[PDB]
Length: 134
Image (cartoon, one colour):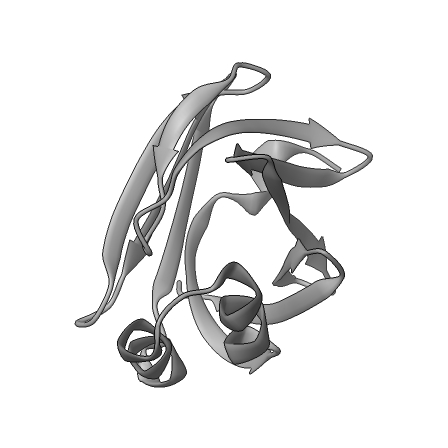
């Protein structure tokens, strides 16, 4: 498996655990309502070691770019400024976020043609499944 195989526009088809993940982060109720009904597309592009991940919906539109392996400042949707690192390892894109002594990991992998995105903080997990928009 490779990082290039994650490229494309992806539509959200299933979500489990989103609200609980947001509660673990301590995100406030307005932003958790907004997440309970937004179904953002994810657009992943990678040019060698350059990665970009964009989220698009009417409620939520965000993007970040990085170099694989290099720490960078990510501003998250909820407004954290994290030190983030993305790496492609063991067939998955792994995005590690650290802020204020806290940590969360977001993993993105292909399973049977679908993009499976797992976010975890302190054992609290959100699993999101996407299908390719083509």
